[PDB]
Length: 162
Ligand SMILES: O=C1CC=NC(C[C@H](NC(=O)OCC2c3ccccc3-c3ccccc32)C(=O)O)=N1
Image 1 (tube, protein in one colour):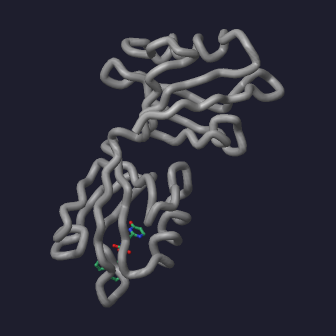
Image 2 (cartoon, rainbow, N blue to C red):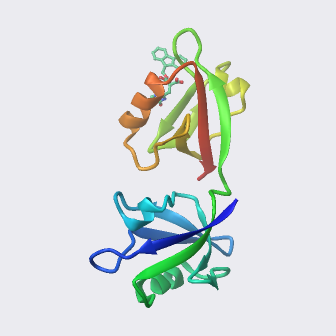
């Protein structure tokens, strides 16, 4: 759904957030660790409907960057729609412990024939966002692989088109 967040700027008047224009909307592209943006729970793929009550519709990435930098006040408010491009696909590890996909730089690149990923219709050219709800955006591939490997039999992956 939609919600309001209220962020307090840090030491340098920053919130740790980079935004990106997509289809005449504005979306969260990068959230800094331990930042005000992380504190209020902003995540890669969240949609920003308003900043300080002003509609973001049609803003360029540069204009959103400017609005954030030049915002007057110690606080910045936003209206957020939670990751509208996100979907889950649930798969099951086979007897060798595999769900059946290859990924590189956090993006699914190949589906293994006659695997659980194949049976459940996992797609390529998609970001791996969460594994059973655990956020893996920005992790190294070996870290993603480790989280996958230690998951139980049910593996639900949250994905987003890349
Ligand atoms: O790109 C990555 C990197 C790390 N993890 C994953 C997810 C994992 N994929 C995977 O480990 O493939 C190699 C695996 C393997 C190793 C040795 C011999 C046979 C087979 C075999 C046969 C069928 C399907 C998968 C496999 C998974 O599908 O659970 N993808």
